[PDB]
Length: 398
Length: 49
Length: 55
Image 1 (tube, rainbow over the protein chains, first blue to last red):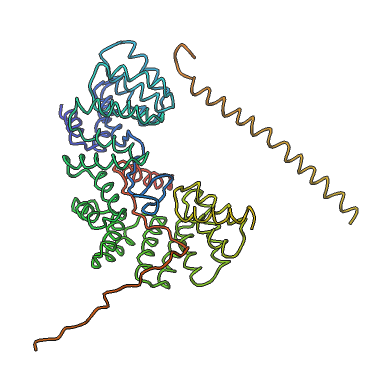
Image 2: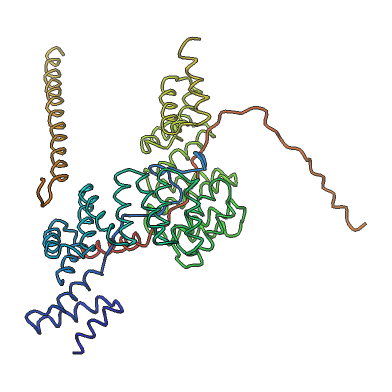
């Protein structure tokens, strides 16, 4: 029959919305057809289907979004599957447990799926005993991304290492394993041993997008702003065309001293920006350009427009009120750093900068608790340790 | 101003009793969130729970 | 006699003689590139507002 074939042939070329209506057009022709019932099911599944976490691949982060280069460096089986886009985990778990007792082996898929249901809720240990048994029978790449996903959320960075060197020698040269191992090294900031693995996901597989930025960002910091451009002009030629990339392409050409593409790339980045909170960050990076040419009147209204397009931009409140202290507005500056700190209770830069305004005045009590948090949020700073010992001589005696 | 000073006190003591009935509910809500997390760590459809 | 072109540069610079305690700025940030799941999940959720804007 031509309707049943055209329904199945629409699923093969994944014309999904043209498939579900034509399949349910066959639904009233029968009391129950098992083939159309699962096809109406499975074409409705793949409309939206995401598996992993929001894995948004940064280039400039260490802890709670901090910057860098001033710190350092049967047929019911798919009927089960309709519950997994609806995320009703417990209801699916009954017929999952019903069917695995119906056939109590030869189903590693049902073994790893029930463990995925347990991780979807929060049953950590019950998942951790579940799909380990499936790995002892079957060699599958996603199961290594299942054992070594729950263990990192269980916070054991050495138990992630053994799986990422076990399956790497049964699936040699595999790509997404070699990206999973260099992603936990950036969590502990082990970039001595992270960026060698990201030189392997670029050795073979020379177009993986999320390991092109995370090398082309770790060269823009630590003073290779020309090599970091080469990783970003190549990422343009794949043809992704975001607004975030014309920001990063604008910054690398300026610091590499290439003054042609340095600023047209920002005007294309001001346009085609999605949210109103997003065009703030392109105005903010434009401010660091404007400090570089020396124009402060220009620079004063670049952070301001970043601030009126988005309040609670904590990196701009600090950055605007260094330009104020250059002019003389002390009480104006000391309130912006006062509210830059309360928006970012990390990120040492307002805390230390409070304790060189409030030290020149003479208030050595608030200028201690200021330069207290500029030690706890970033130790091994130089000019904090030349300031606490400057204050602790005043506190003992004359 | 003397009779005014009586009303500012028992309002403030009612604020003090307002500051006394609040901390007992919070830790028992911390007890209430701990018992939910004890449930969801345990609530599953098999034997040992 | 072709050209002089002698513009003698000083060959010396203003060396520092002490450090000064100064105020430093926040450093410029490179924006992250969102993944193809985050690009899909935002696009789906952005259309989820317009279908509830009419209903």
